[PDB]
Image (cartoon, coloured by chain):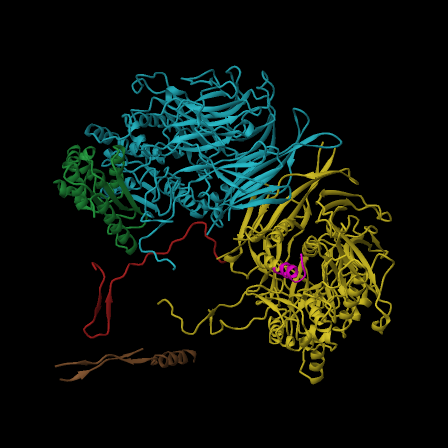
Chain colours: A green, B cyan, C yellow, D red, E brown
Amino acid sequence: SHGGFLSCHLIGQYPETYSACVVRNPVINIASMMGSTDIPDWCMVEAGFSYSSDCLPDLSVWAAMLDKSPIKYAPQVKTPLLLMLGQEDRRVPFKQGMEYYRVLKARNVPVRLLLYPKSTHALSEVEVESDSFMNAVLWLCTHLGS
Amino acid sequence: EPEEAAALYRGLSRQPALSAACLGPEVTTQYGGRYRTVHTEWTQRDLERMENIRFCRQYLVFHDGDSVVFAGPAGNSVETRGELLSRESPSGTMKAVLRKAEEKQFLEVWEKNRKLKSFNLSALEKHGPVYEDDCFGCLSWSHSETHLLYVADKKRPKAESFFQTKALQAIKGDQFLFYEDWGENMVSKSTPVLCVLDIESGNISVLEGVPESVSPGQAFWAPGDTGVVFVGWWHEPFRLGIRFCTNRRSALYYVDLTGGKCELLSDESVAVTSPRLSPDQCRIVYLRFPSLVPHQQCGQLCLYDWYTRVTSVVVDIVPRQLGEDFSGIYCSLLPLGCWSADSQRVVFDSPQRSRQDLFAVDTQMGSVTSLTAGGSGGSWKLLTIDRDLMVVQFSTPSVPPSLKVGFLPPAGKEQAVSWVSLEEAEPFPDISWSIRVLQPPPQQEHVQYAGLDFEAILLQPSNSPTQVPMVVMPHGGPHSSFVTAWMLFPAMLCKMGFAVLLVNYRGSTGFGQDSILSLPGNVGHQDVKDVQFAVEQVLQEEHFDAGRVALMGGSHGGFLSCHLIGQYPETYSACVVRNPVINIASMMGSTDIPDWCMVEAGFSYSSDCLPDLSVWAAMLDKSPIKYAPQVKTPLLLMLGQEDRRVPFKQGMEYYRVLKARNVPVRLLLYPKSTHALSEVEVESDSFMNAVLWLCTHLGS
Amino acid sequence: EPEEAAALYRGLSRQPALSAACLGPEVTTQGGRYRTVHTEWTQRDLERMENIRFCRQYLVFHDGDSVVFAGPAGNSVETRGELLSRESPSGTMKAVLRKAEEKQFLEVWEKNRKLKSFNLSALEKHGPVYEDDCFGCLSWSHSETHLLYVADKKRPKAESFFQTKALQAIKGDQFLFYEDWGENMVSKSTPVLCVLDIESGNISVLEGVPESVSPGQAFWAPGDTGVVFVGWWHEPFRLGIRFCTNRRSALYYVDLTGGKCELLSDESVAVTSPRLSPDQCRIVYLRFPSLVPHQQCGQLCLYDWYTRVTSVVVDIVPRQLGEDFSGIYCSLLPLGCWSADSQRVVFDSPQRSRQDLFAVDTQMGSVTSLTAGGSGGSWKLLTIDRDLMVVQFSTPSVPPSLKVGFLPPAGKEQAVSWVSLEEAEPFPDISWSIRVLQPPPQQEHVQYAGLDFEAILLQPSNSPTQVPMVVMPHGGPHSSFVTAWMLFPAMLCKMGFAVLLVNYRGSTGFGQDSILSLPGNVGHQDVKDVQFAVEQVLQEEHFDAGRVALMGGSHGGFLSCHLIGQYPETYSACVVRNPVINIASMMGSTDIPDWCMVEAGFSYSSDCLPDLSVWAAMLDKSPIKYAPQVKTPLLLMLGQEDRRVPFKQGMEYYRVLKARNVPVRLLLYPKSTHALSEVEVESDSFMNAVLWLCTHLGS
Amino acid sequence: DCFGCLSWSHSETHLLYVADKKRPKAESFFQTKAL
Amino acid sequence: EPEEAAALYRGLSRQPALSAACLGPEVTTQGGRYRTVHTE
């Protein structure tokens, strides 16, 4: 999630350092995630603005949010990526990872997407947790080695 | 009273609606004279179990040459259940029905009074579920009546988990992969394929030769049963919604049964649709759209000669108005039977201003003749034509749909057509409807296109009392129109004492190509002023209370209503919207048609698009959430969870803003509903809630 | 090979069967006239393993006295959910009842739309609606403003003693015993008559029915002043009415306002099927004078509504009346039987081994046969309305067909012209014949002398000296084999077998004297009759006497057990379904205990107690006595959920045979009744039987 | 964890917990009644 | 009254019934020893 956030920055700004990446429910666009989320005050505080009940869009606020999003460095990514998302997520919508996947796919870079029809932010089910861990292990073993 | 309105809604909802009609084989008698049978399918709403029921009816037509001597019923209505597809043989002896009865799908062949064959498609394990939608689904008979052709979902490899236990060829870890679907109302419809079934031996074959980057649909057998001609839709780099959009890349392909590469029968740079074969199996006619910017526009009628392999244009784009009765082709789908007996004329229908008429075009020399001109109005619709016998339906705002048959006269006398009724409908004599033409003032006139005007439809009670409340509603689209057809809700509102206004602003279909290309770029400040001008002009007529005006909308109508109540707070006293668009900027990321917002905002859409700060500024300027603080009108909201076109978070943001502003609002949320809100229970609930909301704030 | 047999069965089971037919309203043109015929068909579908029902419609052009043209007017439309259906007398509206947990809805249709729909479950006025033929009905009022039907009576709510309630049901009566009517009538204890008002939707249950009777087959009285119904006595006990006509019944008439009912017939006998005249002045019904046999000759009784006089039209035929009539053996009259003149009644009944159509004049009391002559065949009257008759025809070589005709005036009814509507493709490799057999004087009955019987023989037409034969006697024991279309005898004749159908003494269609002969001495007379028939058939030098098998069911299984017990070396194989093995043990557990007493020769009474002589006679009649001498292969097929004949009889027979080390194969179907009518179990049983016969005899 | 609890009284005669609030019953306009 | 009988039956049925019992392994301490009994 938020670590995935950091991950989406790390391959964006330092393309040649890392050889693989695995993220779960990342944050891609802060500006879009503001409207469809259960904690809108997380966006303002992290971006540097003060949250209030009466809040309306502003061009400066939108510019600040779009400056810090990891989707800005998307065209420079060249690392293989594995995405894992769940539909029934209220903390972070699954459309952020979908937008990142679309942008990367349009650039012809390897990427693998997994989508769980009934899963929350935690992905805390015995079947899905084991499946995701096995997929991550196989991906890391394949792209790096034994 | 709520009980009075519930009884009124129950009475108006029992009118059946016609779905399809077909003509049977011709039978001659020993004494003399011939007759035919017409099979019609109707649908109705039943509130006792809250379901849509479908039934079939038969009619009998006695004709002597080129005139209809007699017409009557031939039985009772028979209710059917669980029938997906049906197609009668070209000769008429056999009928193929695809039905569902966990659930499984069966393909059945009927001849006379017995069922010859039945095939279980699930057990044979050759493909997936069969497509039954209009855009892809089809069921075609071979010219020898020995094979069947349909479209089915492609089969996916089996999958399993890493920890599955086996008793002592499925790939492991791939059971949660992502497969893209086509969008709204097309869930889990990733990739279709063409399947051919042999009636004699019951063998299913999946054709090979379709390009790997296209999806096939609307396939039909080539002349001589040598191959299959289909329409391929491009699905790379990713798919876009096709529910109400005709601007998706397409091409015409012809493939062989043996295999090999597929040929191209049309240009691949534009969109084509609806290929129809001539009864003499020598020519093909189809619809071609020259641009991909708008989601609805004028089309062209293209002709392809099979043996000569030369393509020509029959009907071309109409800029403003060609003649006094024709304005262009705005129908995406041609009727299943359109060719005449001579195989030289094509019969179709398309809106013309606020009407809908039937047109016939000569293929040898492009000339369009209107079959139904003059009169007060009405909306005709063609259902089928076979051996110069046309079956049509007719309705107005005052009468429910009817049924009629007629004979197409020879060339040069097509204006004189005699219609014989088959099933009349009882009219409502207390509803009056009229058409008013409106000219925009010079200040709000487009620079590129000048002289354009629009119009509206006014529904008022005949029993005139000095104070009549009004309800104003603009259409969705934004490339769509109101024709003078039968609409349930405007009829119900006019029976409670209201007067209804239906505005067709600039940008609607049926007025020419120049009206289509005017709304792109400038959305949110041109049509709003047009609607306001219409409302202001109508109020000059007496017996209209200016203090009681309500507003109704949906989707793009919700967009217009949000803009109207944000810009003119004091005019309207109540507003009802369904699934509105509130923030264009946020809707860009989460939607199945991302090109719509870009095109409407004035920016060209391209793949691999990147956000730009200039683009976001323009999008936020046209959104109706900008005028949210200065809103003081009671509002009713209606939303659905399972909506792929317009997410339900937009209405929630608007609701939160208005709630923080301490403004009386009401929110109704349907846990399982798409953009249509078409389920009987939810539709009745929403209509009843809207009626009870409008009566309280305005009056009885 | 099993594949060939499966393919042949799949081919033969593709023939649809006709269920009902009705005539629509008359339409005139500017000056020919025509009308429509609506027919209901049913068929077996092995892919879904279900019986499918569909509707078809035909079109008839007539000049008034003759049929000019007739042809189809559409395609076949499959329906699902309809239980009852009835068209208005004028033909405008139609009333349907359908099920869709599941609930029942009553729908009223007009033209191309559904006028009304009522949810009978929600009103909570009665229970489920009766859809059977015994009690079920659906009648329109003459004014076409009310509807009448029969529904289960409502029971008080029940509750347990330990029930928790949030901070009018009796506690402890949720497990009481309610007596049902018997086989195929589970949870059908007591019905009531319900009237529905279409205009307002009210439902009212009539009052005035006697508390000791069950009403059924009700129809509106002339003038819509009341309801005329048939009451069945259900005290002290309830006896099964399935395939039984010897049940006490009476005709009653009750007003709508609510009052004491009246009697329109004698209460000491059985009556059935009241039918009202088109001019609403006369009623005809079937009367059975005795309650000893379960099937017998009836008589036609006429009642005049205004003069209140009862008379007899058709009387009981002892042996034979004329040469074409032998009495009335049909329990149910057709829904439309009266002619336009309201002076003649048309019905169908079996005569010897063939079924024919008869017209009877109400005044003169003379019976005329419309379909006399010819080689054979079975006719069945589906409907008559305004002198237009829709009938069905079939033989052992052809599947059922459909025909229409006009009833000619009085005195010229022999010349009837039939116009075909839907022909059926014949099978030209099947030959069928009728052979008349006279019993020898040694086994001739004492009271009745000169009685003979006859059999039906099916053989391949193409003659190739070694042809296996299969013998099957009918059930009943008061039932008959007619020359109609039967699926299994046709299947057997296509595999090289020759089938013999035996109608022994005691079967219907031969007179009242033949029926009364079998009571009192069942077990030795019919066995000897069947054996004599088999020997006489085998006398000809065309069949192989070494290879003879047999089939049976219910009473046929009883006869087959007796035959293999008494003549062990004659037959090489045997297939039996739901047999009767021990009458004495059957007495305790059965829904028709009077059958055992009547067949054994003792009068049945409600106050019945065991006696040693009665049990000794019952054990003497039973075939279990001859079990130790059986040496033939045997196949048993039983249904666990059977009320008519418990499967413990077949189990005891199986155990006795198993202890003796004789080959035997047993199949038990857990959820099937006495009929074994489900598609899956029926196909499985037929395939098992044909494979067993092929294995133990040959190809 | 945030809302849920189960508490014993000191006298050990009463129990305290937290439960969802009850909402009024609702129905549709076209509902048939057992009259 | 039915209520009194129902209450008395509810009171009398509260008594449990012993289905099974078994003995566990022996444990010694630094110097008594003990063991456990598991009852169903």
Q: What is the chief secondary structure element of the magenta stretch? A: helix
Q: Is residue B7 above or below residue B163?
A: above
Count the numbered circles shown. Answer: 0
Q: Which residues are magenta?
A: C688-699
Is residue C694 a member of the stretch shown in magenta? yes
**Residue B682, x across and y down, in percent:** 41, 45
Question: From what the image shows, is residue C102 above or below residue B437?
Answer: below
Would you identify the image quadrant in which residue C298 lies?
bottom right
On screen, residue A109 above or below C513:
above
Q: Name the residue at 31% across, 28% down.
A: B528
> Can the viewer see residue C92?
no
Q: Quadrant of residue B243?
A: top left
Magenta-span inclusion, residue B495: no
For residue C490, side relative to residue E2 (left or right): right
In the picture, measured across the screen, residue B302 lies left or right of residue C595, that is left
Q: Nearer the viewer, residue A126 or C489?
A: C489
Q: Is residue B213 visible?
A: yes
Residue pictured at 30% horizontal, 17% vertical: B447
- Residue B102 screen position, x and y as percent: 46, 52
